[PDB]
Length: 28
Ligand SMILES: [Zn+2]
Image (tube, rainbow, N blue to C red; front, side):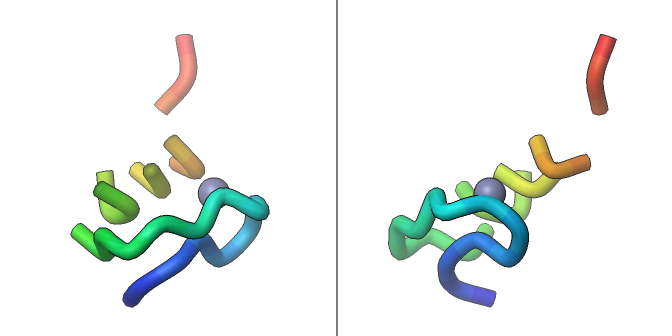
C-alpha cells in the first residue's frame, strides 16, 4: 500500500499514492 510500485517515487501516503498510481494509471 505504502511507496510506489513501478516508479522510484516513494513517499508515505498510500491513498496520495493511490491517486500517484491512478498517475501510474489516465493520460491525455
Ligand atoms: Zn510511481
